[PDB]
Image (spheres, coloured by chain):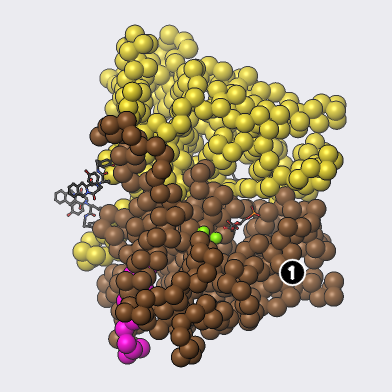
Chain colours: A brown, B yellow
Amino acid sequence: TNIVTLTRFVMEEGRKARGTGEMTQLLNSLCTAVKAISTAVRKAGIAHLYGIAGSTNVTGDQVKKLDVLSNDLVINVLKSSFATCVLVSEEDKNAIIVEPEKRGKYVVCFDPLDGSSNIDCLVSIGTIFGIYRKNSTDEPSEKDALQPGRNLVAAGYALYGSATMLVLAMVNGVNCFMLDPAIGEFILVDRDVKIKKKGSIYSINEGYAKEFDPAITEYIQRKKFPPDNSAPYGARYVGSMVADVHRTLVYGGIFMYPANKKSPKGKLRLLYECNPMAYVMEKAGGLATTGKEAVLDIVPTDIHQRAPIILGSPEDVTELLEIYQKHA
Amino acid sequence: TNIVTLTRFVMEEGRKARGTGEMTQLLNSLCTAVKAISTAVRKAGIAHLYGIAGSTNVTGDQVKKLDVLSNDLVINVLKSSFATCVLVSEEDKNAIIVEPEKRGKYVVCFDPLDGSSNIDCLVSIGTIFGIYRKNSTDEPSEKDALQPGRNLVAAGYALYGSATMLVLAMVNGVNCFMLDPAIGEFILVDRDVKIKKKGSIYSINEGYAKEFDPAITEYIQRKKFPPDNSAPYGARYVGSMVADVHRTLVYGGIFMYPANKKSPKGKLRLLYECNPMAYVMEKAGGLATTGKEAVLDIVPTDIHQRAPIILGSPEDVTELLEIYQKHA
Ligand SMILES: CCC[C@@H](C(=O)NCCc1ccc(O)cc1)[N+]1=C([O-])[C@@H]2Cc3ccccc3CN2C(=O)[C@@H]1Cc1ccc(O)cc1
Ligand SMILES: CCC[C@@H](C(=O)NCCc1ccc(O)cc1)[N+]1=C([O-])[C@@H]2Cc3ccccc3CN2C(=O)[C@@H]1Cc1ccc(O)cc1
Ligand SMILES: O=P(O)(O)OC[C@H]1O[C@](O)(CO)[C@@H](O)[C@@H]1O
Ligand SMILES: O=P(O)(O)OC[C@H]1O[C@](O)(CO)[C@@H](O)[C@@H]1O
Ligand SMILES: [Mg+2]
Ligand SMILES: [Mg+2]
Ligand SMILES: [Mg+2]
Ligand SMILES: [Mg+2]
């Protein structure tokens, strides 16, 4: 019929679903935040920090840092949606308990800004989120954050790259929305997205070679030296999970972040990094595993618990799991 | 002292220069070209393409691609400068001779948009440019663009990443200007840029391992298994040269793209990819070699001649060079 906007989409769901509305309000809030973060990432108005209007010689570099500004934007915007009671963020040691006068029936685990190491060099970065409906009637507490990804109602991420895109995964599938920064609307460009069965790119940090387990080690040799004499896979690794996963989703292949010396249980976080992306991958028709068990079925025991993950096209991930059994 | 916009910076170089004012007009052009491309890259107005105003009878004129657009912006904006006579673009099979009624004395080699494999996945991309002064004194010809990079008077790139940055290198140094997209000005944010002596990140597509020469193989192995038992280098490889070289510049380290079987003499182009980055690296106090000789010393015989390239921290690059030496 005609163009579809995130606002419209999040609403059509609301009609169909016939619910309190909370989720639709929560998702609109999210959007409003991703737009603010995006404009800040692109550094709009930076001339004002460098004294274009002067500064009466009194502006020590005490500007709130992008990483911190993102958290503030997400907390406050979600807290104004009236759809949440518990919020977990990478930037906060404890789960944030929402004021009673504004609480809702949802729990959100998020990474306001992922790709920290790439921040100063201008590489793509992003915001990650997974949403859970409360699972009991006890007074709100971190407890509600420890629900397995298997119980996610919605998940996704915002990629601030060459352009800004919001990928949202819900029970019925995955959709990609492109931010039109000129009017501030996320336009739907890819509907019910599905990952490729087998890709041709593998992504992982090889500087950890000396610490890889026998399975990872074997797998890598295969991509470079195909036992069946097939074309070796190309290698890509941005260093920003949102960016690597996003490419995995749209181009195919596999992305790996396993255990190594300093990261026995892996590095990536379960609540706000592994789970959202795993849900996104599965909802898009791909796999996401620790190498041994599926990421969504893990029962988190701490809000900043780390987990090893491997995700991407089915066959690519299957083959690596194949190798893991071989070594078991 | 106060804010410095690239425009202010380019006008003052000129004053000192005491010349025709042509370089200034040229850099002005480039800037305008860069800002428009950045705006296109970020997808402003995309709502219109998706019917926000209804059927726009758009047909035969299949929408214009970012790559074609960018080239057209750069080709047009440069001609308007009245400061050039020969343009070499990756997108053009032949050097563009500027019509007589618009001829300036400069030759420019550029890549309107680099990292084309990262376009559809929203990964950082950029524009690379290298500028020359007409060597001869006879009718403008492709030959004029066939000069070693040592002859460059100005070179750099516009990186369309999380934020847009234009890096400009000239005889007296390298300067970084952040694009404030709200007013269309580039703000100098890092003056007299120097790369670090030793890094801790290497950047190469290992999917070609099977085809690497013995030196690359040895050096790579040494990065993961530091014979000095120190911490191994972290790995990063975005896939877009600009993003990758840019990271190298601000964090230090080493970027590589040697020759492989399908790429007998490397993949990257000497004129609009390698030379400009080689130039930036040397002005920043870093090195750039093919493995046998300095990139800038090479004399071109084909405007689309490719070449292998190793750039970054001098210590890391020299380490690799001594390995080539040893294996000789
Ligand atoms: C895009 C950033 C805008 C930013 C700003 O810093 N402007 C200063 C000049 C400038 C403009 C663009 C740019 O890229 C760099 C510097 N800004 C505004 O322009 C207007 C000003 C204003 C004045 C009165 C009442 C409300 C507002 C709203 N309003 C804003 O809320 C912000 C912040 C602001 C507000 C008041 C000021 O005196 C200076 C800045
Ligand atoms: C940021 C895109 C701007 C772009 C556009 O696509 N506008 C359509 C509406 C829209 C707005 C925002 C958006 O994100 C998507 C679609 N645009 C303008 O808004 C104004 C319109 C105009 C009208 C009369 C005379 C001059 C201009 C200049 N002018 C422009 O040159 C461009 C292109 C344009 C011009 C005239 C039109 O009828 C439609 C589009
Ligand atoms: O440098 P490393 O150990 O490869 O870490 C990479 C990862 O770090 C993260 O920033 C998370 O901390 C991810 O976004 C990225 O995948
Ligand atoms: O797929 P490859 O072999 O890594 O090619 C990547 C290189 O090619 C380019 O896209 C140029 O064609 C560079 O931006 C990049 O580094
Ligand atoms: Mg973070
Ligand atoms: Mg993160
Ligand atoms: Mg190009
Ligand atoms: Mg290129």
- How many numbered discs sit on the rendered protein? 1
Element under disc 1 = helix
Please tell me which residue is depicted at 85% across the width and 28% down the height of the picture: B326
| Vertical position of residue A104 compared to residue A44: above or below | below
Q: Is residue B17 visible?
A: yes
Magenta-drawn stretch contains A323:
no
Q: Position of residue A64 (x, y in %)?
A: 40, 49
Mark 1 residue type: Leu
The front one of B95 and B267 is B267
Left or right, A221 with respect to A127, comes to right
B298 or B239, which is in the foreground?
Answer: B239
Q: For this rendering, which residue is in front, B74 or A204? A: A204
Q: Quadrant of residue B103?
A: top left
Whether residue B213 is visible here, answered yes or no, is no
For label 1, the residue is A320
- Residue A305 % position (x, y): 63, 70
Q: Chain of mark 1?
A: A
Question: Which residue occupies 32% across, 38% down?
Answer: A47
**Residue at x 37% of width, y 61% of height:** A73
Magenta stretch in the rendered image: A17-30
Quarter the C terminus of chain B occupies: top right
Q: Residue at x 75, y 46 (%)?
A: B232
